[PDB]
Image 1 (cartoon, helix red, strand yellow):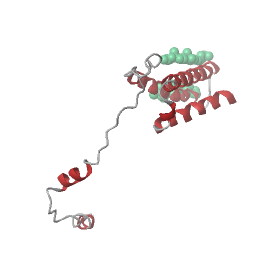
Image 2 (tube, protein in one colour):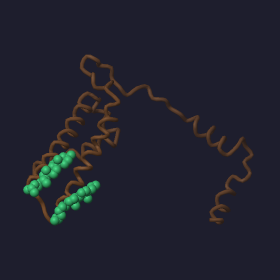
Image 3 (spheres, protein in one colour):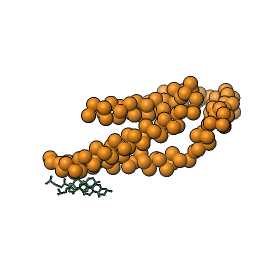
Image 4 (cartoon, protein in one colour):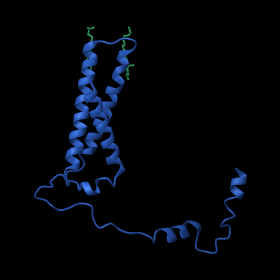
Length: 137
Ligand SMILES: CC(C)CCC[C@@H](C)[C@H]1CC[C@H]2[C@@H]3CC=C4C[C@@H](O)CC[C@]4(C)[C@H]3CC[C@]12C
Ligand SMILES: CC(C)CCC[C@@H](C)[C@H]1CC[C@H]2[C@@H]3CC=C4C[C@@H](O)CC[C@]4(C)[C@H]3CC[C@]12C
């Protein structure tokens, strides 16, 4: 560790400037490019865009399926048919809810710029995997 201290502090031991934090801030924060916007106006049919803060509720949804994914603990070396079919129904309805939510949040959200956010791509991957799971059964 001491070696790491003597192989790092000597790069700028003599600052000859304002301060290490100050010089880094003043030489890195000046290259700032503000963004104009990411929302088309189109308010005749784009009411979805202003609908925010609902995900904070649906975030709870993201944990509910998690509980379902532990319900198979009831399948410990043995299963009850009604419980298993109820779990299948819960999985199907959760996948349908995720699919409809992503469709409604991407139908009028500029699909040209939709691929910019990798989280949307991950959501597309998980929903298509769920669709494959439903179809194969
Ligand atoms: C005869 C054998 C198969 C036992 C039958 C009953 C088993 C399958 C049931 C009875 C009580 C159940 C547990 C009750 C509570 C919890 C806590 C939860 O956070 C995870 C699942 C877990 C750990 C359950 C797993 C399934 C369970 C152990
Ligand atoms: C054949 C006999 C032994 C019945 C075995 C299956 C029983 C124990 C299972 C099958 C479906 C299960 C229910 C499925 C869903 C829920 C909703 C959850 O929020 C609370 C538990 C509750 C209400 C479960 C209780 C246990 C249950 C009724």
